[PDB]
Image 1: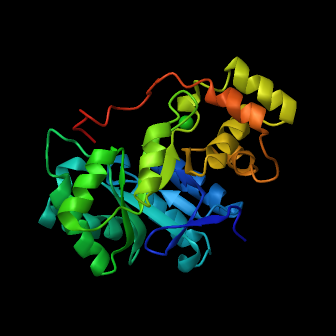
Image 2: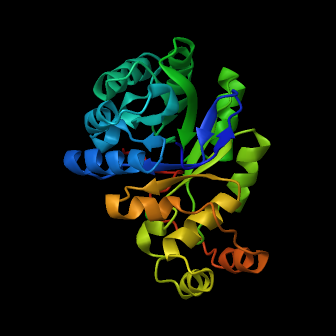
Image 3: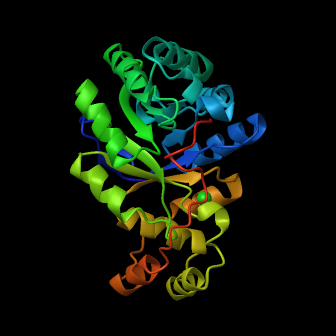
Length: 276
Ligand SMILES: [Cl-]
């Protein structure tokens, strides 16, 4: 049975509000992390062309005994593959590596404004969705203006905008902008690559609730109304990370975590980053 509730996307598909990402995991690590997550009820798995581990994700899914329709699989289009024709080819290649007939969500990994191809990538992805290769399509690291360009030029609104989001960079404005466009915010790096795990405000709250710092950080993120991707969780951590639905952070503690916001971005800059 599933360990997290789901949120409804603007195309009426549903998506688990908590899932496992496998960025920077080796093939063996990826298989083990996915297997461990599926075993404790995680049903969203988040990978990418760029992580080099879609085949390993595919192996773990194939071995899991979990029915395909109960799984939500996300993968991502790398910037060199952006283009009307090339992004359709890239989608099929990801499916082949995953050993799947479809993915539940296909994301443009970065807008890469200097490259200037992301609108044509989206045009291709609209065809990939029409053909059933991706049931939903969305974006990652997009600004409000990037999303408005997609809507204005292709008439299709992303289902999800997956962005860096944690208390040092709480994305208040972009959260509101996503919502205004009916786009779900999906947070990644919710622990700021671990930099927040020994933050005095975070550890004080964790002590008060008798939870871990990661549980506090994940719960805060969920209570903002975001979907969340747990980053590359080790098998020994994933059950703990998913045990975040049996408590609620009071307003004063949400406010305290809100006060940590200081614009610290630990991943790349959406405005300028043109790599993978
Ligand atoms: Cl993180």
